[PDB]
């Protein structure tokens, strides 16, 4: 069998010298049986003389040089099935939810190629959500990558949970929360919250599958957690048809992990230190997220900008890949608005007069223009007084503060936590609500009574009952 | 392929030579002839000193090989093709480097270990035999892996001895014992 | 006498050796002996030279193993037997390190005595999983009102202390240990925080003062001081937090709690830079290894508040990072900032303004929050945060003519700033933290002049003790503030403001 | 006390040069032979015991 | 002493064994050290500079570094498909792409493979990728 003895351990770059004519191919997966169970090395070079240069996916401590290695022959094949759902699964495809051996029937190689032109999005359609704010002010796309901005404090995690529920209703989808550079504390919190909010119901169904990749996990395994998550997603899209939504945590820490492995590989750091292969690797990752004939993966990513130095290649390249960005604000949530979305920061290219229709585009522009004018108005309103400004001007401001309240809707997932039943509102009823609100028909109704509601119709009732 | 790796370092030459000449089964002949032509080459003072020296060109080196193949013929023509290769590779100083390595590979194939009894004095023939016996008695010298045990006298070591073989040494020298004793009586 | 010592020393070279696998130095340069031999050799294995020095072998090269020396090159010389100790780096773990200043190996450098140890456990041990962890409910109290309330800290938690050296960087850390003396007295060993101070790159003269200070405040008896001094070699410095953590795991495992304060991981980084550069492994950004991030992540994620699965115990950590301008931009700060949950940002401006040690608590943050805060202390200090928040903004108009609202904020805020001043090595009980913040919140401090805040404090506390140390004892024991108790407290404070 | 402690250290250093003198005595005598012989037979005893 | 791409044991063994290097290293190569989308091949002595080589991998590559008895190709193709010791055969032509008139209405990738799939290639000729731009005298005043 293909066997070789470890012939160097300079860093975590472990060179294995194999007996001749047992030729490997680049991107193979080697497994070294170890007292650490196994050490999984991934062949990333051939150094000739039937020697390799590999990266590690497991720790390299206590290695006695000359250890025999066995070559699987190709990229690690990571379990897939609906058995993976609700299971935190490690890079080596083993429980870190600790709910024991997954019964995932088939496993599939992690390194994989992006679909052909045909099986890439030729026309893009808007994947629906129950959140009206999302479907208006940053409509989610089919195949699209809409990269969330605005960290937890806006209820980011709860927002993400809401999305999982919405996706399930929306298509029939599933999700996979893949976490890169996880803080093991935060991972604990997420697992506990996710269990509680029933996106992972042990007895019940678990839509989201969890893959967490701690920072402590070696840089090679940090880079490969993302690809593993993606493989599950593509199994969902291609082999279960289902559209999925794949969260990624910091793609900055994705970058950092890739950058480190490049330097380890000896490859010269490119500008700002970031890897020379940054573009292509991201390119693969964000072109395996697209609309095939079957499903479509879509990816919501977290971008840990390096001190808002967007100019830097790692953010710039990230923004180059991201179709839309949803920019939740903590200011907004502090105005009591949950959704915490700040639409004067959230920007999408999926707001076009074709993508969502001309009427929607015009309506959106009006709602935005109302808010923009309202914001500027609030600047001088504080000194001048609203009542001292034009009847038209205070009409706008009054309508706006009511609109602002109308944006807020309880979240279905956290319905238990708030004690307030959430709202799942379809796109058509979203359009209807804002048109009427633009004509301010039922926007002659107090702000508090236009607060924390879904569709326009629902809040006609609430308006009356509040007054009564 | 070679039964043992010396991890190259011009042992890559030795390895290549080893397997090629092993299948030609002419490694003993090669080694002996290589030693023999080397002894009289080294004892040609010009190009037994200047052979080491890299003064020689490519073209001048090739002409050196022609002189060398006048010095002996045959006894593995793969080492004769090696001479050409080495002149072309312009290394002829790490020629004896390769010779030493080839000897190790050759005698490894034969299955023979070389040990040493570095000592500060030339020991008894009783001592020589007893150590040689002791090493075979221990599994350290396994069977089919022969022993050449060479006691050497080194002045640097002051008294006692260190037996070495199998990359395991037992050093019962006075110098080392003295080192620890001195240290603790200065600490 | 000299003879008793001789017998000991000879006893210490009695019992002949019997060597096994050796390597021999080919050439030794720059703390990188390059050894021929050591065919079998665990990674991070300890090897002991015939110069007696110990090393680890970061490069295992194919035919030579490039040992890294933990000491001076003079000792080493060409052709030197390098015996293979055959044990990966391990350090004693056990209660014997309590009240002991030890070197990395574990040898008492204070020489107070050999370590009672139940194991020697390896230096780098993988982080405890998702499910081994549990939410942090227990607060840790530093006896500094601002830290305990404004920046609420728990046990298990890892939180940064980024600030400039010698502003009593060490002093801020030491204060916690002293308030933890109170808790230590408290029988439960989740309250007995067996603190570990990891002094990295710190001269022995300074560390001598530290050791003496701990002893003075009688806290050096549940303390452990891991010492890797300025001159102590870069392998020792590199592995010093790792080995130290393993000690911490023993406490955590036993269900006990402890606090490990790494000061400063910046010098741990520097030591790794020395190692990496000498091992020719490329130095990362700012000539500081790129997988220094990887090291920090491994070390800092062993700090955890366990679940009852692995017994609810913990290993609080407080890494200290030294900045020279507050340059968080710098690669080593950026990495650590990401890994830690919460930050304490200590600032120079405050120092000059008489807050010594000096903390800018506007720029301090917690990302573990008030779940690790006493319920009582939380209740009477929400208000404080908001008043101070306004105070920051309204400090930007302070320097004349001002609306009454702005001026009011300034009155409460200036008094509060004076109240939040603190001097080194003064811990303060929770039953006295709770009253002081209440007064400020009720604006009762406003009346008593700024200069008279100092006088107010001691007097107020004694007055509270005289009037009702029953109330104080209720705050401590109930741990909660009953409305009747705050009613009485409000009356008491008013009375105290009167006299 | 200070000079007493200093004297105790000085004694160790005085005896240190005496240790060196005693080392020279080992290396000259046919203790040099007899004890090397002892090392030889000791090495035999250990190595046969392997 | 020094490192040479002929220190390789398989290279040395062929030489020591006095095995011939005609037309297997004059027009065929055998891959040596490969990784990082560049491959180092031994032989291909009749390789032209910037020729297109077809590997047995299937991968095609453009010679960049023509080195004494070695070539450092760039792989127009995944490293997955490439293994060490593959046989590299000269395509024999400088890198050219099909050029013609009937490419209108069809996407092609750089090689010329229609990656919309549509349009089975209709191209009159192929023309070398690097072409030195027309002279001063070739240019004339713009007006359209």
Image (cartoon, rainbow, N blue to C red):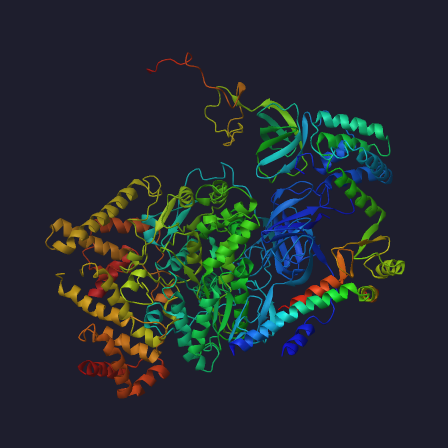
Using the image as rendered, state which of residue A192 and residue B76 is in the foreground. Answer: B76
Percent of width and height locating residue C174: 41, 71
Instruction: Tell me if E101 is positioned left or right of B184 in this view.
Output: left
Mark yes or no: residue A221 visible.
Answer: no
Dividing the picture into quadrants, the one containing residue A24 is top right
Using the image as rendered, state which of residue A186 and residue A77 is in the foreground. Answer: A186
Q: Which residue is depicted at the point 23% across and 78% down? A: C456
Dividing the picture into quadrants, the one containing residue B151 is bottom right
Placement of the C terminus of chain C among the 4 image quadrants: bottom left
Q: Which residue is depicted at the point 77% across and 34% down? A: B48
Placement of the N terminus of chain C among the 4 image quadrants: bottom right
Instruction: Tell me if C388 is positioned left or right of C106 in this view.
Output: left
Q: How many marks?
A: 0
Percent of width and height locating residue A309: 37, 47
Using the image as rendered, state which of residue B164 and residue D20 is in the foreground. Answer: D20
Percent of width and height locating residue C159: 42, 64
Instruction: Tell me if A34 is positioned left or right of C272 in this view.
Output: right
Percent of width and height locating residue A243: 47, 49
Instruction: Tell me if E40 is positioned left or right of C215 in this view.
Output: right
Outermost residue on the left side: it is: A388
Using the image as rendered, state which of residue C227 and residue D5 is in the foreground. Answer: D5
Outermost residue on the top side: it is: E137
Q: Which residue is depicted at the point 32% across and 52% down? A: A133
């Amino acid at each position: 069998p293909i066997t070789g003895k470890v012939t160097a351990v300079i860093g975590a770059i472990v060179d294995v010298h194999f007996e001749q004519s047992e030729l490997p191919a680049i991107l193979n997966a080697l497994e070294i049986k170890t007292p650490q169970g196994k050490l999984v090395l991934e062949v990333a070079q051939h150094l000739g003389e039937n020697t390799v240069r590999t990266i590690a996916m497991d720790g390299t401590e206590g290695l006695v040089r000359g250890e025999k290695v066995l070559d699987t022959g190709g990229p690690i094949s990571v379990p897939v099935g609906r058995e993976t759902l609700g299971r935190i699964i490690n890079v080596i495809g083993e429980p870190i939810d600790e709910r024991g051996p997954i019964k995932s029937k088939l496993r599939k190689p992690i390194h994989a190629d992006p679909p052909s032109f045909a099986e890439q999005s030729t026309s893009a359609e808007i994947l629906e959500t129950g959140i009206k704010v999302v479907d208006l002010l940053a409509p989610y796309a089919r195949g699209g990558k809409i990269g969330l901005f605005g960290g937890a404090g806006v209820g980011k995690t709860v927002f993400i949970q809401e999305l999982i529920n919405n996706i399930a209703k929306a298509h029939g989808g599933f999700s996979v929360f893949t976490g890169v550079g996880e803080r093991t504390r935060e991972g604990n919190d997420l697992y506990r919250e996710m269990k509680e909010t029933g996106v992972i119901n042990l007895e019940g169904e678990s839509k989201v599958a969890l893959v967490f990749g701690q920072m402590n996990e070696p840089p090679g395994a940090r880079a490969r957690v993302a690809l593993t998550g993606l493989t599950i997603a593509e199994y969902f899209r291609d082999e279960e048809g289902q559209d999925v939504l794949l969260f990624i945590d910091n793609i900055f820490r994705f970058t950092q992990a890739g950058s480190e492995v490049s330097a380890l590989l000896g490859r010269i750091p490119s500008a700002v230190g970031y890897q020379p292969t940054l573009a292509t690797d991201m390119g693969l990752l964000q072109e395996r997220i697209t609309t095939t004939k079957k499903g479509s993966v879509t990816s919501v990513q977290a971008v840990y900008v390096p001190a808002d130095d967007l100019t830097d290649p790692a953010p710039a390249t990230t923004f180059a890949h991201l179709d839309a960005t949803t920019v939740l604000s903590r200011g907004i949530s502090e105005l009591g608005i949950y959704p915490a979305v700040d639409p004067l920061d959230s920007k999408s290219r999926l707001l076009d007069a074709a993508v969502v229709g001309q009427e929607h585009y015009d309506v959106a522009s009006k709602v935005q223009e109302t808010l923009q004018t309202y914001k500027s108005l609030q600047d001088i309103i504080a000194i001048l007084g609203m009542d001292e400004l034009s009847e038209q001007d205070k009409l706008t401001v009054e309508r706006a503060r009511k609109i602002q309240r109308f944006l807020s809707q309880p979240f279905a997932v956290a319905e238990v936590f708030t004690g307030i039943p959430g709202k799942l509102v379809r796109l058509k009823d979203t359009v209807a609500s804002f048109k009427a609100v633009l004509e301010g028909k039922y926007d002659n109704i107090p702000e508090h009574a236009f607060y924390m509601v879904g569709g326009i119709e629902d809040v006609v009732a609430k308006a009356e009952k509040l007054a009564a | 392929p070679p039964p043992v790796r010396l991890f190259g370092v011009e042992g890559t030459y030795a390895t290549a030579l080893y397997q090629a000449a092993a299948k030609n089964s002419s490694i003993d002949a090669a080694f002996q002839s290589l030693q023999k032509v080397e002894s009289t080459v080294k004892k040609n003072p010009k190009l037994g000193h200047l052979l080491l020296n890299p003064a020689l060109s490519l073209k001048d080196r090739n002409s050196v090989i022609d002189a060398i193949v006048e010095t002996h013929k045959n006894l593995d023509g793969y080492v004769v093709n090696l001479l050409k290769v080495l002149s072309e590779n312009n290394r002829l100083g790490c020629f004896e480097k390769i010779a030493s390595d080839f000897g190790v590979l050759n005698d490894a194939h034969n299955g023979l270990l070389k040990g040493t009894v570095t000592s500060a004095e030339p020991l008894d023939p009783k001592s020589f035999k007893r150590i040689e016996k002791a090493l075979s008695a221990s599994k350290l010298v396994g069977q089919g892996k022969s022993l050449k045990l060479e006691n050497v006298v080194k002045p640097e070591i002051k008294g006692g001895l260190i037996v070495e073989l199998g990359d395991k040494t037992v050093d019962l020298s006075i110098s080392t014992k003295i080192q620890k004793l001195n240290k603790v009586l200065e600490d | 006498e000299v003879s008793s010592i001789l017998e000991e020393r000879i006893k210490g070279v009695s019992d002949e050796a019997n060597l096994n696998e050796t390597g021999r130095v080919l050439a030794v340069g720059d703390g990188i002996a390059r050894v021929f031999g050591l065919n079998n050799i665990q990674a991070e294995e300890l090897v002991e030279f015939s110069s007696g020095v110990k090393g680890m072998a970061l490069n295992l090269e194919p035919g030579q193993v490039g040992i890294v020396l933990f000491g001076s090159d003079r000792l080493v010389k060409e052709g030197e037997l390098v015996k293979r100790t055959g044990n990966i780096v391990d350090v004693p773990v056990g209660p014997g390190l309590l009240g002991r200043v030890v070197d990395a190996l574990g040898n008492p450098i204070d020489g107070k005595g050999p370590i009672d140890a139940a194991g020697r456990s390896r230096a780098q041990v993988k982080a405890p999983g998702i499910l081994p962890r549990r939410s942090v409910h227990e607060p840790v109290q530093t006896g500094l009102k601002a830290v305990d309330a404004l920046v609420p800290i728990g046990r298990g938690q890892r939180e940064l202390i980024i600030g400039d050296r010698q502003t009593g960087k060490t002093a801020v850390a030491l204060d916690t240990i002293l308030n933890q003396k109170r808790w230590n007295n408290g029988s439960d060993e989740s309250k007995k925080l067996y603190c570990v101070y990891v002094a990295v790159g710190q001269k022995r003269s300074t560390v001598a003062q530290l050791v003496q200070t701990l002893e003075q405040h009688d806290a050096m008896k549940y303390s452990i001081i891991v010492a890797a001094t300025a001159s102590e070699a870069a392998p020792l410095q590199y592995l010093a937090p790792f080995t130290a953590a393993s000690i911490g795991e023993w406490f955590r495992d036993n269900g006990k709690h402890a606090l490990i304060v790494y000061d400063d991981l910046s010098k741990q980084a520097v030591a790794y830079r020395q190692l990496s550069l000498l091992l020719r492994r490329p130095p990362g950004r700012e000539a500081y290894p790129g997988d220094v991030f990887y090291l920090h992540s491994r070390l800092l994620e062993r700090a955890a508040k366990l679940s009852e699965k692995e017994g609810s115990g913990s290993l609080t950590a407080l890494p200290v990072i030294e900045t020279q301008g507050g340059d968080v931009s710098a690669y080593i700060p950026t990495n650590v900032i990401s890994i830690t949950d919460g930050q304490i940002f200590l600032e120079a401006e405050l120092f000059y303004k008489g807050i010594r040690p000096a903390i800018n608590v506007g720029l301090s943050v917690s990302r573990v929050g008030s779940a690790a805060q006493v319920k009582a202390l939380k209740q009477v200090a929400g208000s404080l945060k908001l008043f101070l928040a306004q105070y920051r903004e309204v400090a930007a108009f302070a320097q004349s003519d001002l609306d009454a609202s702005t001026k009011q904020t300034l009155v409460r805020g200036e008094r509060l700033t004076q109240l939040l001043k603190q001097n080194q090595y003064s811990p303060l009980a929770t039953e006295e933290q709770v009253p002081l913040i209440y007064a400020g919140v009720n604006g009762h401090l406003d009346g008593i002049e700024l200069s008279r805040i100092g006088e107010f404090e001691s007097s107020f506390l004694s007055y509270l003790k005289s009037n009702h140390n029953e109330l104080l004892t209720e705050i401590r024991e109930k741990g909660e503030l009953s409305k009747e108790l705050l009613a009485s407290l409000k009356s008491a404070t008013e009375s105290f403001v009167a006299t | 006390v200070r000079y007493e402690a200093s004297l105790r250290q000085l004694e160790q250093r005085q005896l240190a040069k005496s240790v060196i003198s005693r080392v020279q005595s080992e290396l000259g005598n046919p203790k040099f032979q007899e004890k090397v012989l002892q090392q030889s037979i000791s090495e035999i005893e250990q190595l046969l015991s392997k | 002493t020094k490192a040479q791409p002929t220190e390789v044991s398989s290279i040395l063994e062929e030489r020591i064994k006095g095995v011939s290097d005609e037309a297997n290293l004059n027009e065929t190569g055998r891959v040596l050290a490969v990784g990082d989308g560049i491959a180092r091949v031994f032989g291909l002595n009749n390789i032209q500079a910037e020729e297109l080589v077809e590997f047995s991998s299937g991968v095609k590559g453009m010679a960049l570094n023509l080195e004494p008895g070695q070539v450092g190709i760039v792989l127009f193709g995944s490293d997955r498909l490439v293994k060490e010791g593959e046989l590299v055969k000269r395509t024999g032509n400088i890198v050219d792409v099909p050029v013609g008139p009937g490419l209108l209405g069809r996407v092609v990738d750089a090689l010329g493979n229609p990656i919309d799939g549509k349009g089975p290639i209709d191209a009159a000729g192929r023309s070398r990728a690097q072409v030195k731009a027309p002279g001063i005298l070739p240019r004339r005043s713009v007006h359209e």
